Image (tube, rainbow, N blue to C red; front, side, top):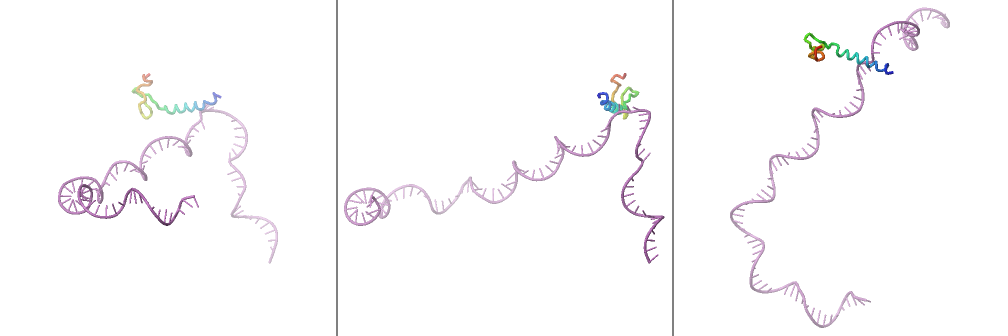
Length: 49
DNA sequence: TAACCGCCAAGGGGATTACTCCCTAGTCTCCAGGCACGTGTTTTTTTTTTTTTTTTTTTTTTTTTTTTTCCTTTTTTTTTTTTTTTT
């Protein structure tokens, strides 16, 4: 029952999470930006690694 | 049974006369509360914007793959041809 029930909302959460960050991009200056170019992080993971 | 009347006796105080005196009527003269006029500052009414809960709407529901079965109209009204009866 626990295997059958929660896996619908698990896949829905995975699809929602992959749709929200589908264009969060590391650029050539080391910064992290989305599709519109808004700055999210100056370095990826706050260390650029 | 004592109201009432008649008779008699006694006394108490209101009316009268005179003297006084003192308080108010009258008349100036100054001035101040009583009153006519204007208005107020609270009270009610009305708007105004928000608040808070209720109700309604809308959108969503892991992915991939392989087999069958049933259905993919249907009754209901209108039209048009055919057949039978009559003069």
